[PDB]
Image (cartoon, coloured by chain):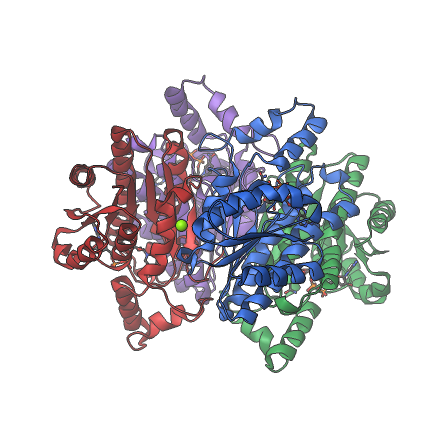
Chain colours: A green, B purple, C red, D blue
Amino acid sequence: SKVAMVTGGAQGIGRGISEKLAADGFDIAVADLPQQEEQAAETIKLIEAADQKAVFVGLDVTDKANFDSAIDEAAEKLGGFDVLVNNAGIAQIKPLLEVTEEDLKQIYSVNVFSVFFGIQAASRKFDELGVKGKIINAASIAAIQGFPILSAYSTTKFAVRGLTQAAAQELAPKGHTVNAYAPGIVGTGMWEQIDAELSKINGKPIGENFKEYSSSIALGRPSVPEDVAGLVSFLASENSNYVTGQVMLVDGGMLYN
Amino acid sequence: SKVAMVTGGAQGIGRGISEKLAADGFDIAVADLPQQEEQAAETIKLIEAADQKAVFVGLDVTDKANFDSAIDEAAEKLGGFDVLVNNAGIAQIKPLLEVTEEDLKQIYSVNVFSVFFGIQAASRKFDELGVKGKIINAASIAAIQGFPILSAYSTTKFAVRGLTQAAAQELAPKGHTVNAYAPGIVGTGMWEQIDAELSKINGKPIGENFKEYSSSIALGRPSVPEDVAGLVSFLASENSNYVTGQVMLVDGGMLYN
Amino acid sequence: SKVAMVTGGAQGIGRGISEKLAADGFDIAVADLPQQEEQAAETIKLIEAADQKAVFVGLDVTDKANFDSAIDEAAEKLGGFDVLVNNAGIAQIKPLLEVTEEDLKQIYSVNVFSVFFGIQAASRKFDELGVKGKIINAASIAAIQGFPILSAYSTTKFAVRGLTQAAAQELAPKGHTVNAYAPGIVGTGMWEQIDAELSKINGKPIGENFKEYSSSIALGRPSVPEDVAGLVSFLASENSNYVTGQVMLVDGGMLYN
Amino acid sequence: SKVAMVTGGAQGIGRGISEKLAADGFDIAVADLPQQEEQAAETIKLIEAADQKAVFVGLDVTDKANFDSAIDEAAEKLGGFDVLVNNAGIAQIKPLLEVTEEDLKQIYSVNVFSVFFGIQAASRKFDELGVKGKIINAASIAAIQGFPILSAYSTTKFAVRGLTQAAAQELAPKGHTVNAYAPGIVGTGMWEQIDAELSKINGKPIGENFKEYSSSIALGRPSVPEDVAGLVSFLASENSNYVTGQVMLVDGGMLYN
Ligand SMILES: NC(=O)c1ccc[n+]([C@@H]2O[C@H](COP(=O)([O-])OP(=O)(O)OC[C@H]3O[C@@H](n4cnc5c(N)ncnc54)[C@H](O)[C@@H]3O)[C@@H](O)[C@H]2O)c1
Ligand SMILES: NC(=O)c1ccc[n+]([C@@H]2O[C@H](COP(=O)([O-])OP(=O)(O)OC[C@H]3O[C@@H](n4cnc5c(N)ncnc54)[C@H](O)[C@@H]3O)[C@@H](O)[C@H]2O)c1
Ligand SMILES: NC(=O)c1ccc[n+]([C@@H]2O[C@H](COP(=O)([O-])OP(=O)(O)OC[C@H]3O[C@@H](n4cnc5c(N)ncnc54)[C@H](O)[C@@H]3O)[C@@H](O)[C@H]2O)c1
Ligand SMILES: NC(=O)c1ccc[n+]([C@@H]2O[C@H](COP(=O)([O-])OP(=O)(O)OC[C@H]3O[C@@H](n4cnc5c(N)ncnc54)[C@H](O)[C@@H]3O)[C@@H](O)[C@H]2O)c1
Ligand SMILES: [Mg+2]
Ligand SMILES: [Mg+2]
């Protein structure tokens, strides 16, 4: 089977992607923080229910060395490495005038620097194994339009968008492709947090902010990991071999770029 | 089963899309100009070889009435109608200052008005059958960045881009999605034509223009109908359900949007 | 004195642009439909009040020959021709499924073919006069994001967007630049018509659709011609000499591209 | 007289902007590294030659505390504060696979974090003075399309693009606007550096990389500070009052977005 690593695969969009890629015939390397291993258990169970090989790989994407060994371990255990999905990331909700250098340093490390490290490690591995790989990064609608109150987060996603473009161009001659998926409003822990932090600011009751930000989706429904998985499935398959440097929206109809 | 109509399916990108969707398990209605029914023989041959039902449908996409009946016929012959691919289209190569009103009327009818007609007929057929359909339009890199000497063509593709966004939002409540594919340099009959005409204009030898316009492709190789077929496969599949109003580039890396 | 022709200058944005460019030192050729001369009386008044020459020129931008004669007349009566603002245009409001071929031919003629003709005529005159000119087209937020119910209109603006790009690249070697302005919701006769047609569709009282569509403008206020004139002033000035092929948003904060 | 602070105004585009704004009627605060004071003496001369007041303010934009005191000092010395131009920035030239965390921390601090700091300090001063202000950020064509070998730098500019959008929406209620200028290839000390570094990488002789990258400019020639100052002049004037959250390209025709 082909091998793909999904960072942040312990839960949310990461888990959904892992389950889907497994159904597509990929053996999966579920990479996420070491403390998230128990949480990853379910993700692992889903991969194995799809009749594929799964292994958890402890990783803090903010650390290059850890990312390099994380990918070596994954390739070793699964006997290959063909796709890297840089899904791991965090969100920050805070008025622009309140953002601190501390906030910035932290979110750029987890959301941007990590992608540089994952791209570099994926590249080394691909070449080492003598194969053409696929790198898939998690952008967002916030990478296409900056969102108020989520300025720090938005800027890191824009950075990911720009990185996807530059990296795809530098790795293209080697035959590797780099694309990104941009989901809309996905009811995961990230939004329970966003909605919770928004509530503390505007006073709207819990869950209410989620509904308002969701009221604009053309298809009239908030998203679930499966929706995002569908696009990532394409980005990992052979059908996307001629697509590179793009950031594709899977937002049910929110932005049209 | 699932039924899809591919206009301009008698050759080039249209044929490849028909063959791809056939492999995906779609019964195909190859819609093209009556004059191309013979040229379309091979296409129907490629479809039946993938063990799917294929029927030719005489259609001049510029004629609304013909498009309405064309879809009625396809839905009656194949027993259903789930996907429409507005692929039929033409190219014009001419310096801006030389473009005539007749050039404009001609190209806008085939490249733009036709997509409106197709979108309307498809939407009505989806509703009659009680199906949530997928409409896929043929955009192009020229729909993202206007190209000199191909201004008329570029403008129609930009129109398709805008139409794709507008139609997606308008048809979302019925559950229908509208997306587009934007290929780069695809070595089909259309580019033989483009290279030939550009040759007469700038004087460069035959084939040289084709190479010239291809020297920017990150992946380092021009495109074939198969490359585009890959994206359309995703757009016609269930994996793209939460994607709408988007114009996705399959250009090997030329524009990044 | 520097000379600028403003098509559709009898009222709305065209009138605002005329008055502004006059204030900037331009003599203005107010080009509009013959029956609009009386209406243009105010535009001309506003222009002459800035110690500048103003002349009404009968022009139906949908006719190539008339555009040529109009620019010739403007150049001869004002003694030069430095800037052409392709502002004339119309709006159509109608569900996508109701859009007829007649509607399409009409709106594309007025909003798109007209711009080709305008660009061609302006380019000729510039060269004839041995000067480098500025062509400024009227785009719209609808050229950046298609709007439902105004699908035909949106597609024409996207076409204008593409035309601006293609033309800028094609005319650059001659030193001419082609840019466009993209206003948001401006209270003119065009929005009176849009609001009125929307009202017929959703039953909202007159003025409410305008208010609703304007409720999300970041700067918290609908637009007036003067706002747009601000950008066009830049685009007609020496300050924009190194800007070309761009579609610039002056929408108070609606779309960000 | 109105007051504007131009960071990195000791030379290059910053100097060009300071001179232009001075010419438009603004008193200028030239903010740059203390070591650049002597260098800035040239900028100060160009400003005073316009019969406008000028002062140098020692500022390392990466230091938030320093940025707050610099704006205080600026507003106090010039008796006002209406415009802030976040122009200070650096470039890095290095293959993606070689980018280090040290490079990233470095370039993001100077190119992105500083902008957050400037916006915050500007906003606070604007409100303190009870005025509506304009914030203008230095983006780049690299903020619109990521460039190979300039990945780190590109990603920072994309972040600035996102920041400009998010800040615009967040500060709009107060009446402040935030926009950005995106220069193309400007022959300043920065490109001297980029060319020199590119030279060591691809072996091309000195100066050839500058020409190579410039070859594609529609208007046929590289840019000078004044080309950029033209757009900034618009961005600092009342003509841009209804424009916000935009990143406008002044690249002579390289990217069209
Ligand atoms: N939820 C949404 O609506 C939405 C919209 C757009 C984009 N995204 C993006 O999709 C991705 C997944 O988001 P989600 O909703 O599933 O989030 P989530 O919080 O549910 O899951 C994120 C996972 O990332 C892991 N992680 C965090 N920091 C890490 C680090 N330093 N090293 C390794 N693993 C780390 C977490 O342990 C967690 O399992 C993110 O990049 C997010 O920005 C989400
Ligand atoms: N070839 C490329 O490099 C390229 C790049 C981008 C986009 N496209 C788009 O993809 C589509 C297919 O292009 P292609 O290369 O396969 O072209 P092609 O010339 O090989 O095929 C075009 C098909 O369109 C049919 N057709 C033309 N006018 C028609 C009409 N009025 N009614 C019905 N059928 C009609 C023709 O019979 C023909 O089979 C077009 O819309 C084109 O704009 C092509
Ligand atoms: N009103 C808005 O909110 C808005 C937003 C974006 C873009 N625009 C664009 O700005 C431009 C001006 O719009 P407006 O609000 O001032 O409209 P308007 O209806 O107030 O003015 C349009 C002018 O165009 C002239 N005109 C129409 N058809 C013509 C033809 N065939 N030949 C010559 N002149 C013709 C009319 O006589 C009229 O004076 C249009 O291109 C429009 O699409 C308007
Ligand atoms: N040169 C180009 O072609 C080009 C194209 C697009 C965008 N830009 C952008 O325009 C801006 C100006 O570039 P340039 O060509 O004038 O560069 P430059 O090197 O000529 O000038 C940059 C100035 O920034 C100052 N500076 C650097 N770090 C600083 C810090 N931490 N604190 C305070 N001041 C600091 C320097 O002292 C210097 O005077 C940058 O943001 C750059 O990214 C340049
Ligand atoms: Mg697929
Ligand atoms: Mg100006």
The residue shown at (54%, 30%) is D214
Name the side, left or right, on which B187 lies relative to C121.
right
Q: Is residue A53 above or below residue B92?
A: below
Closer to us: A56 or D203: D203
Name the side, left or right, on which D80 lies relative to D73.
left
* Residue C49 picture location, percent across and down: 21, 56
Q: Is residue B86 above or below residue B227?
A: below
Closer to us: A13 or A170: A170
Closer to us: C195 or D115: D115
The residue shown at (47%, 24%) is B209
* Residue D44 picture location, percent across and down: 56, 46
Name the side, left or right, on which C137 lies relative to C1.
right
The residue shown at (60%, 66%) is A185
Q: Quadrant of residue B194?
A: top left
* Residue D148 picture location, percent across and down: 65, 37
Closer to us: C22 or D75: D75
Q: Is residue B66 above or below residue B216?
A: below
Residue B227 shows in this picture: yes
* Residue B94 picture location, percent across and down: 34, 30
Regarding ligand 2, which quadrant of the image does it lie in? top left
Total marks shown come to 0
Residue A226 shows in this picture: no
Q: Is residue C88 above or below residue A195?
A: above
